[PDB]
Amino acid sequence: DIKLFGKWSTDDVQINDISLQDYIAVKEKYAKYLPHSAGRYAAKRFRKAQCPIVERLTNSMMMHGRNNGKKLMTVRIVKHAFEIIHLLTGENPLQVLVNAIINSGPREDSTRIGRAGTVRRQAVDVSPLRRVNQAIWLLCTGAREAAFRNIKTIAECLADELINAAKGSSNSYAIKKKDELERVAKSNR
Amino acid sequence: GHQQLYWSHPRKFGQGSRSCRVCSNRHGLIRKYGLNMCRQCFRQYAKDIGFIKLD
Amino acid sequence: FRKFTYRGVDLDQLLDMSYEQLMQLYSARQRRRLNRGLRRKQHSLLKRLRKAKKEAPPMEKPEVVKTHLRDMIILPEMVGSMVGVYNGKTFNQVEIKPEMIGHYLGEFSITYKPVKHGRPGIGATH
Amino acid sequence: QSVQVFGRKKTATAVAHCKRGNGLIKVNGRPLEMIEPRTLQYKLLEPVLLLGKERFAGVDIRVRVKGGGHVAQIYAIRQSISKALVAYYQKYVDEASKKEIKDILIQYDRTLLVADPRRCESKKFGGPGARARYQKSY
Amino acid sequence: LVIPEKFQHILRVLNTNIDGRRKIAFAITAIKGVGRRYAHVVLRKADIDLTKRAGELTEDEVERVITIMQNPRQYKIPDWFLNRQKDVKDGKYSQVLANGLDNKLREDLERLKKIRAHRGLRHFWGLRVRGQHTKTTGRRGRT
Amino acid sequence: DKLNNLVLFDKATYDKLCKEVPNYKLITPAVVSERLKIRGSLARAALQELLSKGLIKLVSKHRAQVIYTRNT
RNA sequence: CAGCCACCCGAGAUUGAGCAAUAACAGGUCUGUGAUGCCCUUAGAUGUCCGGGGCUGCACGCGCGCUACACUGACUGGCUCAGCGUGUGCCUACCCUACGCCGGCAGGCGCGGGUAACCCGUUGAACCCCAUUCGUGAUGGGGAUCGGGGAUUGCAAUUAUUCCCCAUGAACGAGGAAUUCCCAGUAAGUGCGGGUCAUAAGCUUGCGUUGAUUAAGUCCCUGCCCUUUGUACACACCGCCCGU
């Protein structure tokens, strides 16, 4: 068996994006008992998607010059809130994780386009890899600010943001960021 | 009475008389392995000391 | 009116009191010179100050002493007189008072100085 | 018997002495279930239960470790265990199941047999780090 | 010993008012010298359970603490562990509470200027005691 | 800024706390502090005391993550 | 085709640096030098024998950097993993440094261990491994702002300069415009070492330890002037030049 942390089942995930399981994978054979395998995917290209996304999380809520070099703390803090989503929604955290990655994942962004002008922006399609990168970045930014200077501890601010982003609820900071991206895509055609 | 008074105060911590062993120069003495030179003489005379650059 | 003392003792008591509890009265200074020992060129300043102290003019201060050496002192026998201490080019005149004990003679030689007075003017804009 | 063929990660290494014993795996006087970080135990039980806890049928494996960093020792202690299992399973017993378990753990990951050649580079002067340089003064 | 209802805002020093919201081992930091590891050690060797809170602060606790802070030799504590060892201008060895008596000792600006000492002049202008060299750099005071 | 919180022992730590923490499904010092208006420090202290009483099920313990669930 | 991109094996399918052209600068160094050019210096010798102050000053402007603003955490302490090195010696005491007694703090004598992978050393180390008050504060993030005392190398710690114990919580709620630096064991966090050295690091130079989403692209607004082009410049645009 290959269950996550030996307690969360991995034979239950359904991405439901027709063909996106090659760019968001927790079932893949690279998915291991723990999300700790040291950094080896960042060297080359399109190898980052071969990462077990649990590792990408435990390294994305791992930032800001106070956490770098403390990866075991990140693995402890992901065990935390994995066993907490195990009880908050009464379901496997991988299901809500794939729901969050399939909804928060942006499609339309706005960028400067042109060789001779600088007046406005143009709508662009954000590829699956960049969309998961910036979605996890928004999730981690919210989870940092939701427990920053606040009495609320980690594994619950992250937990709250994850649950209210996984169901598509717009109350999430990540989902409001997604809506802002979509609306700025509307307003810059 | 300077003949018996000469060299009264032992200046042992200072390198005024223990300066670079080459000439009347200071300001950058290094005692690594007891060189007792400044940077100038060491770098210009490092070929005979045995220190080479292959790093 | 106001009351000043040296923690229950004076120069006379400290002269009578031995160095045993003097070290307990000593803050941290002038103790290890005993263990280290005193060197040469160090026997004339005490004689000179004592000789000056022996004859004190009536209604006049003890005669000025020109000293070029910062001599470490171990006893309060200096207190009660005047000293001409070093400034850098002259000899400045010092009245000794009970603050001398508990402090070193070299701590009365304060000499440090600016260059000149001016403001950021025509030359300096940014 | 010493069929040890290193098993390494960074500057820390492990040597997996293997013999016909009790089936208990020892790490320098302490069981693999209890290691100082108290966090990578699953990383150590991964190989055995991935290939099968039933494989050990009287094999005493003592791994001796030396090097810097605890987590640096791990990924090599388990690599040493996998190497010792490979040596035992290559010395006498068949290869079909050996190739089966090898394919399974190879698709599981790559850091069980072949070492990571990575190592800490030197630092270049004129900066705080090897690649980072000081701030420009305007 | 243990009692749910003993929470009072004020401790008595010189009939002045202090804060009483802090927990034990931290509610007696309101005294100038008591606090830090001093209060920690007196509560540590006071032979009482330290899990108590502000609400369970008994009057016997306060009385024993006041007695222990009056003189340090209750558990043979030397005088230097207090902020005031042998005093200046008097031969005492203890710190005095309230204001107008201890703070009278701190004013140390005129007599050193009599002997033209540097320390007194430095404390006369409110300059640095640690010896922070001042050339142009510094971002405190006028802006 | 201004430190001012509940430090008084009254009908807030036993009543409405021992009568509303057991009935909820997630119990955390932060969760108890937020949902029951109580202080997180005293929440931890009371949770330790009631664990000593033995009326919870503990999964794991940490400085910031002590995992409790209903047992009785 | 030269080559580029993917893939299986393989330790490794771009490991990092010193060498680096022709030719040149009026860029810094005469305060690096027993390598040196008329002026003060012709013994009235800007230290020179002895040596007692000096780049050791206060109102402020984004000069490399420093600990932080906190609950991914300082914090009782549990467990335990480092690698380059540096080390008793010519007007060179002072270098590391295994125990008894004492002394919280540095340190006294001894039996010895060290020219060295023999001695500290198994650098038991150090970051982390989260059982302690901690809960949004002036207390425990933030010793940043007081006076006393033991004292080891230091005749000479005067701005407790440097070895600590008590008390001192100012300011900082991650901070405008302009804006350094960073692609793999890298950035980043983290401590040890060498340089200076009374025993000395907020600096620099090495080392380990822990250790990413950062994109395998374009030339914007940054420089680098390669090709075409114009020239009345060639002292080469800091050029040339017209007129009152």
Image (cartoon, coloured by chain):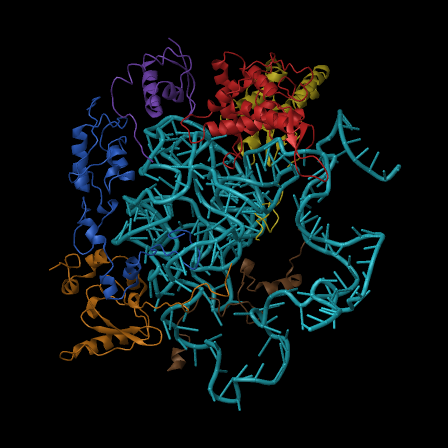
> According to the colouring, which chain is cyan?
G
> According to the colouring, which chain is red?
A
Which residue in the rendered view is the most extreme toward the left?
C1
> According to the colouring, which chain is purple?
F
> According to the colouring, which chain is brown?
B
Q: Is residue E138 left or right of residue E58?
A: right
- Residue C111, percent from left and from top: 34, 68
The hue of chain D in the figure is: yellow
Q: Is residue G217 or residue C71 the one in the foreground?
A: G217
Q: Is residue G212 left or right of residue G227?
A: left
Q: Report if residue D3 is visible in the image.
A: no
| Number of numbered discs on residues | 0
- Residue at the spot x=50%, y=13% of the render? A89
Question: Which quarter of the figure has residue E22?
Answer: top left
Q: Is residue G190 left or right of residue D107?
A: left
The hue of chain C in the figure is: orange
Q: Report if residue C85 is visible in the image.
A: yes
- Residue G163, percent from left and from top: 37, 51
Q: Is residue A25 or residue G225 the one in the foreground?
A: G225
Quadrant of the rendering where the N terminus of chain C is positioned: bottom left
> According to the colouring, which chain is blue?
E
- Residue E15, percent from left and from top: 15, 38
- Residue F63, percent from left and from top: 41, 26
Residue G197 vs D2, above or below: the answer is: below
Q: Is residue E86 or residue G78 the one in the foreground?
A: E86
Residue G191 vs C35, above or below: the answer is: above
Q: Is residue E108 left or right of residue G88?
A: left
